[PDB]
Amino acid sequence: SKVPGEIAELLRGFPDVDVQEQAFAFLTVDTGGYPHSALLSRTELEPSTDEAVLFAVVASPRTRANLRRTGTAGLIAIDGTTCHHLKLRMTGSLADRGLLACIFSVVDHKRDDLGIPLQPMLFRTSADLAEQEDWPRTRDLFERLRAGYE
Amino acid sequence: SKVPGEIAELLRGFPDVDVQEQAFAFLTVDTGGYPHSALLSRTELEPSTDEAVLFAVVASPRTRANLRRTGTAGLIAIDGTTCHHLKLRMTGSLADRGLLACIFSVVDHKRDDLGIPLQPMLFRTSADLAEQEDWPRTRDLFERLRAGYE
Ligand SMILES: Cc1cc2nc3c(=O)[nH]c(=O)nc-3n(C[C@H](O)[C@H](O)[C@H](O)COP(=O)(O)O)c2cc1C
Ligand SMILES: Cc1cc2nc3c(=O)[nH]c(=O)nc-3n(C[C@H](O)[C@H](O)[C@H](O)COP(=O)(O)O)c2cc1C
Ligand code: NA
Ligand code: NA
Image (cartoon, rainbow over all chains, first blue to last red; front, side, top):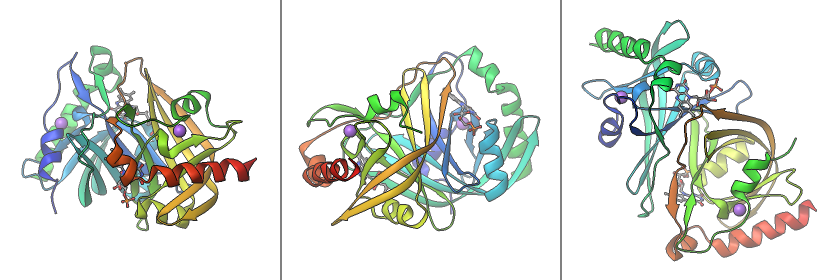
């Protein structure tokens, strides 16, 4: 399958600082079988150029361990009247200090739409966040991912 | 443990129609071990009066089955600068047609706060939604839950 078109458009590209962005719930499963979440943004989510796969860069330690243990993940993405629910299977990964760069195949996509306009989770980017989430290293890892995938 | 105070305040009460409300990501795990999500609101989430436990009413079929299979769940709740991540263990349930009324113990709470103001997922209630999610039956089930818990 592929990254759904509307989701590729929601995630593609990287924000500058001081800009309103959607926070995407990035889901995993912990060792007791409980669902687990982290917030990611366009900075840590990028489709491949052909949209076949979804790349992610994850800093949060428990999410990273969950991915290493089960290889399963999911995403919530909000766009207009649609809540997109994704399920993701990790097919490869690359570690760089506290960051895990991941390649995901989409294994399921549900368009959850009741005809009711939705607002996404939102936050404003900042120079502090750029430091907390190590944007320079995330960017580098995404280019390493792009290069290896191709 | 108990329902965290800030989360009890976010969930308590029931909205009328045509009102802006937060949509809470309600998480489960499916049969292949993938995280799974549904959107719920204050209409389908209510703390016990003593805040010891969290009641929920779930209509979405796969979420309901996931709960029946694993008894695990989670929640995302947004409040100011804090993203609240909850993990939930189902301790009892009651079925009424297509609805599953659930009692959850909180097994974990993480306050995820980077000092960056957050906007929750939002939607406006409506008479159609009241019908789609069967508010009269949800309300009844919550009173049945309150009664049995006490
Ligand atoms: C606005 C905001 C942005 C965040 N961005 C990221 C991010 O890009 N990468 C990340 O790993 N965690 C990020 N987080 C933090 C995760 O949501 C948080 O660490 C979560 O509890 C997951 O941590 P854990 O997997 O170690 O439990 C962000 C949090 C907020 C509030
Ligand atoms: C605005 C909005 C409100 C919703 N409210 C509810 C709800 O109260 N209860 C519910 O079970 N599903 C609700 N949903 C639908 C779930 O998010 C959706 O069915 C999801 O795909 C879970 O279905 P599944 O568990 O069968 O896969 C809502 C969807 C939207 C867009
Ligand atoms: Na991106
Ligand atoms: Na409520």
